[PDB]
Image 1 (cartoon, rainbow, N blue to C red):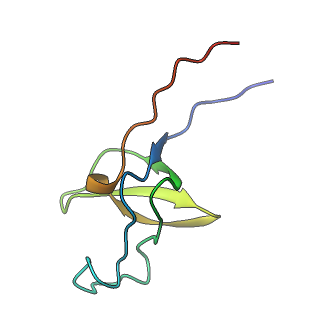
Image 2 (cartoon, rainbow, N blue to C red; image 1 turned 90 degrees about the vertical axis):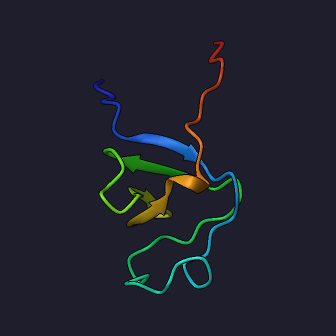
Amino acid sequence: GSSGSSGRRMVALYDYDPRESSPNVDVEAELTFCTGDIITVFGEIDEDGFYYGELNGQKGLVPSNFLEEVSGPSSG
C-alpha cells in the first residue's frame, strides 16, 4: 500500500483569473481556480514566477501569490 507524497496541495488564498490578472500569455495552459480551490503543485517556482500543479483533472500553471501551503494538525 504505497502512497508516495507527490507535489504539495495549496489552498487558493484568493480567486485567480488568467483572463484579467494574466497579460493573456498562453493562458490556455494556465489554470483558473477560485478562493479555497485546492491545487496540487509540483516542483519549485519557475524562472517566471509560477507553479505547475493539477486541478479538476487539468495540468497547467498557478500563481504562487494566490496559494498557501496547506498545513493542518492531523489528529486521528
